[PDB]
Length: 490
Ligand SMILES: O=P(O)(O[C@@H]1[C@@H](O)[C@H](O)[C@@H](CO)O[C@H]1O)O[C@@H]1[C@@H](O)[C@H](O)[C@@H](CO)O[C@@H]1O
Image 1 (cartoon, rainbow, N blue to C red):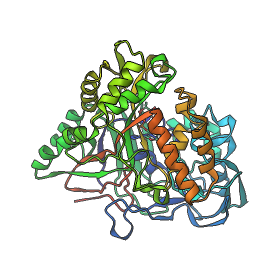
Image 2 (cartoon, rainbow, N blue to C red; image 1 turned 120 degrees about the vertical axis):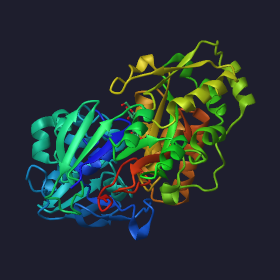
Image 3 (spheres, rainbow, N blue to C red; image 1 turned 180 degrees about the horizontal axis):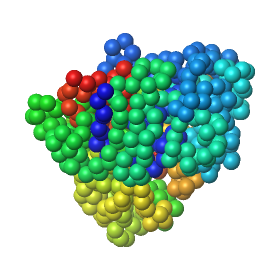
Image 4 (tube, protein in one colour; image 1 turned 135 degrees about the horizontal axis):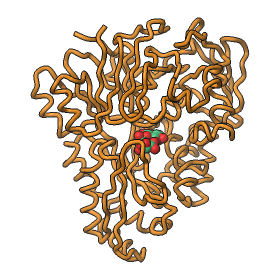
């Protein structure tokens, strides 16, 4: 079989699947591991955006009541080191010890804040396990299909510990670990003992090429089979080569900028709001995205299903109100830094250059500060920074509650003093079933989010890849690459 060569924007600092949650980790850990339930993006001929959930490590499952789901595990599934998958591995994956309890904070810093209100799993037998929540949760199934729920081997993971496991991962997935050179490459090889569709590449190499121009050159020269994280300005050149093409899709993620609200100038909402109200998103979408990016009506996305609000108004744009907020905030004209890891995010620096000019027109002076991969700056040296959030559930709970809620990092680490009402609503939507009360609570949370501006949503990126026409592979509407029954050569 052909070896697959990928030129990527970046690499995660660990292959521990929860710590690898980012724009760059899932395309790798999706190959090493499996989940109990998987999303089939290609269900019923869909162009990589189907919402259908299908059996994966769980052959079947059944919701018992408002807070428990029983899973019947596929038998004779082997981890890469030979160990057979059992309910004990699944129980460990979703345990207090490894994932969501207080002891897990050191190993998986965001484990607890991104998890449901789990109770300890119950192992019924070697192939039967029940996942439970202490309080009602109708999100167990969507959680279990998500990037939080890749199944790790209990004994091997405990032996190494989360850090060393992150450098030598073992999973049940179609590709097994070969090597990891931090900040340079990850190499995987075919797991020919895979339980599902057999791997079609002999090897996969994820080679970091941080500068997108160099990545495009690598595809043109024949060094890479597929490249990631391009902008729509690269489409015409790549498609001019008869043996190459672009493959793009709008993904269930939003780009944003956010603030270190421990900094004096951002403790209060006024200047955060001034900066938010001066962003002309449609002009950025036209200039940098060739109309392909999508601007959402607040923290509100169609993948939320029953908790998506299609009637919501656009996020405000008001240059004159922004000018008045700069004056009322007492802002004295001092430059404010905005950190970016180059173009880790497609259009990060071009968007920042536009926003710097928009902010100059309201009297705020912003300056770019770049940081290298793996060297995220110290928190107290950051003021503004760019970020993104993958919308990882078929529900509005994610990402507003896990990221911006009372137990989340935006309030605890980055100092957002959220109104008490916002936190009360976060607690309510966590346990309520779908209905008018829950739907209205998310809309009020969205309104407070826009009023407070702890972050400023820019748009959903149009994720552009480029590939050799002789490498058959279709993108999916999420920040990952799927190769199961979706990778062939010739
Ligand atoms: O690639 P990202 O946008 O964010 C990562 C961030 O996690 C990491 O600290 C930083 C330094 O290496 O690099 C990127 O900015 O990944 C986010 C993730 O942080 C978030 O938890 C998830 C759900 O909201 O969405 C991702 O897109």
